[PDB]
Image (cartoon, rainbow, N blue to C red; front, side):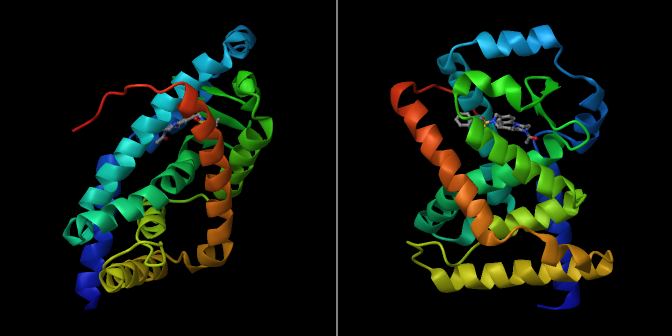
Length: 234
Ligand SMILES: CC(=O)N1CCN(c2ccc(CN(CC(C)C)S(=O)(=O)Cc3ccccc3)cc2)CC1
């Protein structure tokens, strides 16, 4: 690939993210002043773990839908065989959701955008998963310290997904090629934006995997007893 082709890949990935980011950064930022009152938090805390599960399940399913859409728009992804598209998304879609969450997180007061307002970790008390919730908040806080641009998120999350080391890939070489081109795109763009400094500050690949594993385990326990049907966005 040439520098023009690399730059075209950059622009393409960034457009794909802009179109599938689900919530606009501008809207997330403007709504930071909109925070759940004490009585609203109490209202959430009083809800059954089952109600909080179905609400959270709905929001997670929706978020995954947008991540899948993002993948489908990535140059080359649709050219991979069906098995490999599934392997990559099965392994990475929830990891991308966790990265995307940092945009909806306010480090100033440790709150997250949830059902239209910002709330702290105590909003989720009824789940009885305080360790997991706290880890998700800590992770988001770590990422917010980097002041990720929209385009850095676009390129970083593309690379979360396009990982040739995922077990079960039938065309590993094709995935390797896509991953390498995306690494070129990411590194080239960091250079063009004087943002080289962020690479060393990104969380180790193992940190995101570890958090996602803990997350999924908790999700499986809820979804096993309480499945839910969710709207899709074509
Ligand atoms: C793209 C974007 O900016 N957004 C806005 C953020 N949104 C979103 C927001 C909150 C949740 C709730 N949980 C995240 C923790 C911070 C508590 S949770 O569902 O992960 C909590 C949970 C629930 C059940 C079991 C384990 C953990 C899920 C999705 C996604 C879409």
